[PDB]
Image (spheres, rainbow, N blue to C red):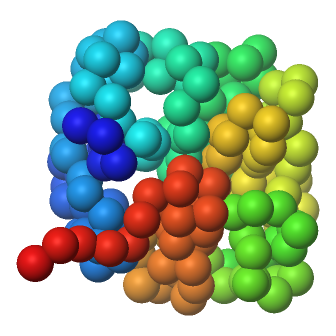
Amino acid sequence: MEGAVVILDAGAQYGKVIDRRVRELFVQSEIFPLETPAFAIKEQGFRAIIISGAPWFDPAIFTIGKPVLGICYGMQMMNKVFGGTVHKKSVREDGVFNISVDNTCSLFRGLQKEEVVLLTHGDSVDKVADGFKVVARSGNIVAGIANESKKLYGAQFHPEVGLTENGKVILKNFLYDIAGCSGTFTV
């Protein structure tokens, strides 16, 4: 329903890690099946979407005018849906890397120009879809993308894990500032 965040996660945790972070920030969240149709999300009145993780998802989750945070595989899909491409197996090993961050991007507000983040082995963006800016990187590796007018944001790394030093700040930026979720409950 309204004011809540829907989590579509293709990974081994089935939304649980991302869901604990959203809870910790006092925001209502529902873990949904990844193939949940975009129209169903709109009809329920969800305020935002977090997609993370070949599994089938509805490409229209990116096109319905709701704020979306794509994490890792979710960022790759976001890029793909808007005409971008990816490198296969470009990240060979899991690691905690210091990366360059665009500080003026909505998502990375309050961060330093350099940040320590967890990147998992796998794929990474090649050609960046038109309308997206690169907002984080290390070398050939695009670590973040943003279409600010559309409120579509991608992070290659995993902000939901404590190993990403200021991952909570990134999620706060998305949920509060970008999506306008209130971090308040009524007891």
In the rendered image, residue 55, in percent from the top left (x then y), is placed at 33, 22
In the rendered image, residue 64, in percent from the top left (x then y), is placed at 54, 18
Q: Residue at point 32% right, 24% down? A: 41
Q: Quadrant of the N terminus?
A: top left
Q: Residue furthest left?
A: 187
Q: Is residue 160 above or below residue 96?
A: above
In the rendered image, residue 151, in percent from the top left (x then y), is placed at 68, 41
Q: Residue at point 73% right, 33% down? A: 150
In the rendered image, residue 169, in percent from the top left (x then y), is placed at 57, 79
Q: Quadrant of the C terminus?
A: bottom left
Q: Residue 157, can we see it?
A: no
Please indicate whether residue 68 sits to the left or right of residue 10 in the image. right
Q: Residue 80, can we see it?
A: yes
Q: Is residue 41 above or below residue 154?
A: above
Q: Nearer the viewer, residue 152 or 2?
A: 2
Q: Residue at point 72% right, 18% down? A: 82
Residue 144, picture quadrant: bottom right
